[PDB]
Image 1 (cartoon, rainbow over the protein chains, first blue to last red):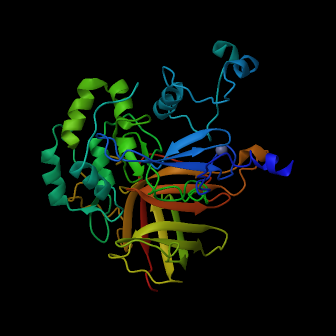
Image 2: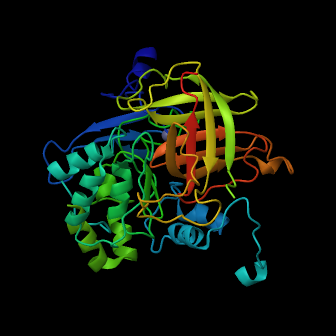
Length: 60
Length: 49
Length: 144
Length: 150
Ligand SMILES: [Zn+2]
């Protein structure tokens, strides 16, 4: 009953960084994006998303 | 409206793209009219209504 | 995507960052030199930013000259500097890093692109709204 | 006739703005000799080499020619009017950008704070009633200081 209970415990992945604060919940429960390798005229940005309470903002 | 609005946005995000930024417009009136927190705020509320 | 398409870039964007530096100081001679570069100007020389020990002008003063004189764009410094908030609020020692302009006059804040364009909260979008394309195009050509 | 906006002699609390500082500009922290009012200000150290704990004289005037209007410019280098104290070691032209206070407590407004900008140069003045006659305005104030390294 333990082992079959364990089989949900983490799905298959992760990430979380816990660096950027979220102004909607003070907790730094945030995720970060590495994208825009080249793109156009828009500068490559680091995008940060807060898992809880759904917040997303940019390095810029 | 506040009670209705909870139905419209179950995501609870109040940040939406909308026309006419009244805040900037209202602010500009303050920049123009020179209203400040150390000046009285003479107003007729019904006129507002 | 209800956003501006214009964007000042590269050399121009870098020198603007350089230009917003606190250590930027100008001479009267160069102010006249800078004034002639203007695509448009009131014809009325501005007051020195400094009088003693010697008369001087600041780059923020002069950038604000470029700016049209009855419109403002607020806060989005959008630069790494300071502290993902909380810190800059410590205590409203609120200048330099964060961007703020009043009556066409830049108070503080190193510039970014999110300020400069192709994004929400950009100066470019509001100038387009207030000043219109024609005034904004002449300002833009002038600044460049 | 020379309706000075402010005058006081100030003492340097700090010349090191949070350590990191900057090259041509540095932010001083000062306190008035009443020791009831304090001040922080950005300065050009290169033209005015401050020392820590120094005793400074500070004056503020929104005008130069006796009290009459002048909030204009072509600042006219050729003025010959002795109207200016100019005799002070250091002068700046600027605006007040922010005012702090607290009137929600009932009349309170008890420990009024003023923030000022001279060409971008930030300033903070704190005081119960020293700023009771001033408020945030467009560029008009002239700030004059002397008594360097007294
Ligand atoms: Zn959050």
